[PDB]
Amino acid sequence: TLEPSTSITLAERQQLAYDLSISALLGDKIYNFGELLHHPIMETIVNDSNYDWLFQLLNALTVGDFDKFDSLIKVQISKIPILAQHESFLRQKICLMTLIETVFVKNIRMLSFEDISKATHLPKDNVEHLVMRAISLGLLKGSIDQVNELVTISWVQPRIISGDQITKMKDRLVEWNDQVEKLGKKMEAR
Amino acid sequence: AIRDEIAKNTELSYDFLPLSNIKALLFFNNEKETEKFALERNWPIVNSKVYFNNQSKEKADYEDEMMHEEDQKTNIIEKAMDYAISIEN
Amino acid sequence: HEKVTIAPLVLLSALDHYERTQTKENKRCVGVILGDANSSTIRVTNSFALPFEEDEKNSDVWFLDHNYIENMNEMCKKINAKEKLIGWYHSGPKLRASDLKINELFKKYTQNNPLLLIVDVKQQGVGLPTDAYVAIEQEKTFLHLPCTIEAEEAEEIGVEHLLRIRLTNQLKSLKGLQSKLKDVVEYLDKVINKELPINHTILGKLQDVFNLNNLQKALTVKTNDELMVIYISNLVRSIIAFDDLIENKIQNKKIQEQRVKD
């Protein structure tokens, strides 16, 4: 975030962004590839010459297609399975955080193996072992249910995205608006 | 008046039953006359469509009617605990 | 982080010299505090004002004399030697370049980070007329430490003699409920719609409260098991309400005895 410090030319900003790109490929820590979008990194580079890898992985999390990003890269980073393993983790971390506040307005905490199967494009057998790997890395806390095919996970790690939870934070206070009358008047009457 | 009495109890007790028990137990003569009783509240008789005839539905979310309720208001429930305020003071 | 504890003697003593100088809204008063900043809980046992002069049309104009500060430190060594300069306070709601640039001036005579204080003269809203703010070198931002009000045994009761149940305790509960409503609606509506400030750094902390009817509907089935303790409280209370009839029946013998004596 520091404008005055680290003053470099335009050509060196692309080389610095290249090190920032390859560093986030091999790990999921500190948000995701979309973190550099708001930072003056992705906006200071060019969208071609294989510098768009940070932008391609932004929509690749929702689409869930590895073949699109694999065709635009080289053999150096594509020969390591860690790239494909941690990329699928960020795709699930978006869905694992939908249990508290993302889409459902009622804040009902529930997840099923069928919903995550369509999001991660994996069968029911692979998604059972995949949830344990995300919890073991210290992402979120919770357990699952194989008998009833249910996944119970809370929400801890914040994201950089906005606009999904803005409407609900006011909607949850609307329920507080209807509670000012009944207990406000009856308490003052005593 | 007889057919308006028996089948009130069949709601909770009887889970399902075909048209044979309707003609026998309730003593109905002509067919398709029960369909006239089936009009508004949607009677696909296959299992249990009741609550049209013989009182009504079970609804849901009963609040602010008579005395104490369940979901929204704890105040009238708390009013029993607050009833000692006017007695002690 | 650290903590702040300020006795009520320090808070009101800072407001007195504000009016004694006939200071209007165009001027503000700046002063220094004393205590022990070494521990994790910052305690302020003393305060002294300063002849602070400021221009209302320019935020870069201020008057601060360190010779009065050097003399004040020498005068305190003869009163309380255990007290050292832990920072400085100031009056007025507004924060301008006058109070921001002088934070490094008091740093020369203060070993720890000077603790900034905004003393509200009108006492507008909630509690805590004075807020304890600390600055970081790494970007600078004003953060508020968990400032609390605590004093000794004789100091807490001393103000009680000068100033001098269940329904009243519930009155403060509703005031805290509206505090949850009014703080979020006014702040969140400022970030959205018109004039988006630079944010999503604070948003991570805001939504950290909402995850854990603000809390959880997933325990609704388990809540009935948690409510059981409340139902248990009514088991004995039904007899406790009947225990009032014990004395009520014993007191019946008194009036019945009065009819015998009459």
Image (tube, coloured by chain):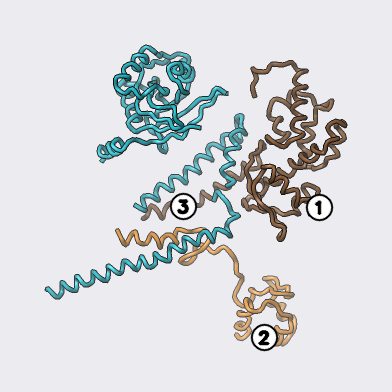
Residue A132: percent from the left, percent from the top?
72, 48
**How far apart are labels 2 and 1 at the CA level?**
53 Å
- The colour applied to the residues of chain C in this rendering is cyan
Q: Same subunit under labels 2 and 1?
A: no
Image point (38%, 22%), residue name: C84
- Which chain's residue wears label 1? A
**Residue at mark 3:** A181
Q: Quadrant of residue C87?
A: top left
Q: Nearer the viewer, residue B37 or B7?
A: B7
Q: Chain of mark 3?
A: A
| Residue closer to the observer: A98 or B19 | A98
Q: Which chain is orange?
A: B
Figure check: A129 above or below A7: below
Rounded to the nearest whole Å, what is the CA distance between mark 3 and mark 1?
51 Å
Report if the CB atoms under discs 3 and 2 are less than 8 Å apart: no
Residue displayed at 32% across by 31% down: C9
Q: Look at 72% across and 25% down and name the residue there.
A: A41
Dot 1 corresponds to which residue? A123
Name which residue type carries label 3. Answer: Glu
**Disc with the residue nearer the chain's start (3 vs 1):** 1
Instruction: Tell me what hue chain A is rendered in.
Output: brown
